[PDB]
Image (tube, coloured by chain):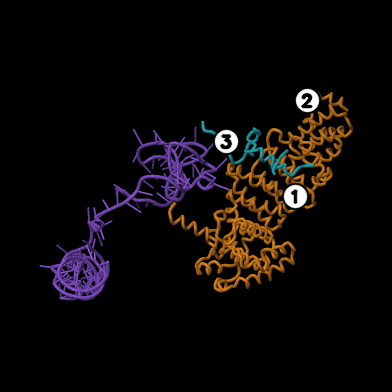
Amino acid sequence: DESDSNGDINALTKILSTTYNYKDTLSNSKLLPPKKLDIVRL
Amino acid sequence: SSLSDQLAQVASNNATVALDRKRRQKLHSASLIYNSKTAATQDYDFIFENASKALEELSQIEPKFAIFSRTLFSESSISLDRNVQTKEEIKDLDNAINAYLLLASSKWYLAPTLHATEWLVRRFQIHVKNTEMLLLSTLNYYQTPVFKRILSIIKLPPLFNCLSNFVRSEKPPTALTMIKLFNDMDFLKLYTSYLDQCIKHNATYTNQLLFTTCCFINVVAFNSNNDEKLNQLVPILLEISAKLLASKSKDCQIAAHTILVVFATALPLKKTIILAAMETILSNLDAKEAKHSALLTICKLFQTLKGQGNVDQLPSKIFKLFDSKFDTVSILTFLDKEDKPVCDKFITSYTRSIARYDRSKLNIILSLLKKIRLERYEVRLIITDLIYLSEILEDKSQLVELFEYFISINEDLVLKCLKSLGLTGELFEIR
RNA sequence: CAUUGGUGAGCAGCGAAGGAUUUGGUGGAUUACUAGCUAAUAGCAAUCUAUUUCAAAGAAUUCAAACUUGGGGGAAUGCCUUGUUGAAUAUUCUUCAAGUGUAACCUCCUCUCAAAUCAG
């Protein structure tokens, strides 16, 4: 039965489905996220 | 395994099939109103007559409960016990019971509902035989002592395991137990399977739905640190939000709106996921009462993000969907509100999408840009695209008033980006 | 005063985006690893059923057969054994006695202790 062959209401679901990491870690946002420091002792 | 655990498993297989008569006076004697000494001595017919006596008033309140008189509350539907049926028949019994439960979930403050479902408890052991739907349909009533009675009767599944201390308790189950109940992950997969079931069946009423958002929202409140637990919490909430927006219902729309608001404000998603959120929000923004919430959702949504392309222009489908479901003068009214909430990161992104596809209403942009004190890079980034529409779009008096406003406010900012792009006297040679 | 006691505060000291504890569940080893099932040289493992059945092969203590019982008594009523009596057709069965006969069946033992308490 299940086949793929104005805005559609499947639009959130598909872009969820093509994502596993939903945090934008590919950003290099050049802002600092709060509460969590990526910090390494050297 | 041990023998004793392998045999106490057979208790779970036959917890309702009363074999000794003491098992009957255990299995029949628990019900939703009657005390167990008077609940022990109830004939089946006597309970079914009270069942119809509440069911007729319920069916007269709304006709959708009339069909359970044809099947569940039939006069022929007394003698049949569940365990005598095949599992393929038992599946249809459970289908009827479940569809009745989300139906009566609205009507549960009525003593008609309490007197109707008590027979179903007693005729079909739905405190034990199908207790996941019994609890999920009636989860929001945690303050009401009808539910508190129901807690002392339900064989508790592992999924509802916060209330293992609250069965046969005096004081009602607290609000924090609802969060700790919902703070599990697989419980949330059950609550999707409840709410998605209610969506296609269109049995979604307001009070339980407000309890849904208050629990899901408090889950992301509790997961403000556990960002990896949050990253496995996006699939359960954003699916409920998306499938929520496919409803005709407007309370469900503002429910999914609250979900998206608190989720983006607690965890920064990618920009494209927020574009998906915008498509699903605007693609079902039809009725009036959801528009005031849904505008503030995108106001929060574009503020929740930061990155490369932070205030970039929207796609042409997304922008035309937005300018179909809102006018220009909708946002021209909204920015002149005295609440005036901070949609700062949205306007400077949306004016560019006007400035590339439409370009027809930049007097509207002048009105827009005088309204809000924006961010520093934002005004500069608008002015660069307006330099682009100076160069490639044919120069017009609307843009002349735009840049005259931009010389009235932050002329030197224009001078700096003009030293970046183009020349100063060439911009006087524009118009 | 030793506290060599811990609480309790603390500090030096240790010290990389925690430390310390407690426990549930499951998996892995705890002998040195050649596959599962069946009717098994083979077939199965999606199946052995409308070849599984014919066939062959296949019957001694002429009835050896508690190696097994807490110990004494006895062992009435049973049984066993021969002695002995009748009947039927060389053998069972009726009848009867003798048995420091007897894992049936009756009783006695196989409980009362420098353990403790308690008067003197």
Q: Colour of chain B?
A: orange
- Give the side of residue A31 with respect to residue C112, left or right: right
The image position of residue B230, as x and y in percent, is 60, 44
Residue ID for mark 2: B421
Q: Chain of mark 2?
A: B
Shown in cyan, the chain is A
Q: Chain of mark 1?
A: B
Q: Chain of mark 3?
A: A
Residue ID for mark 3: A38
Residue that protrudes farthest toward the right in the picture: B397
Q: CA distance from mark 1 to mark 2?
A: 40 Å
The image position of residue C61, as x and y in percent, is 24, 55
> Residue B49 occupies which quadrant of the picture?
bottom right
Q: Is residue B209 visible?
A: yes
The mark closer to the camera, 2 or 3, is 3
Q: Which mark is residue B321?
A: none
Q: CA distance from mark 1 to mark 3?
A: 36 Å
Residue ID for mark 1: B293
- Amino acid type of the residue tagged 2 in the rendering: Leu
Is there CB contact under 8 Å for labels 1 and 2? no
> Residue A9 occupies which quadrant of the picture?
top right
Q: Depth check: give the residue in front, B115 or B316.
A: B115
Element carrying mark 3: loop
Dot 3 crowding, Cα within 10 Å, few <14, some 14–19, many 20+: few
B170 to C35, vertically: above or below: below
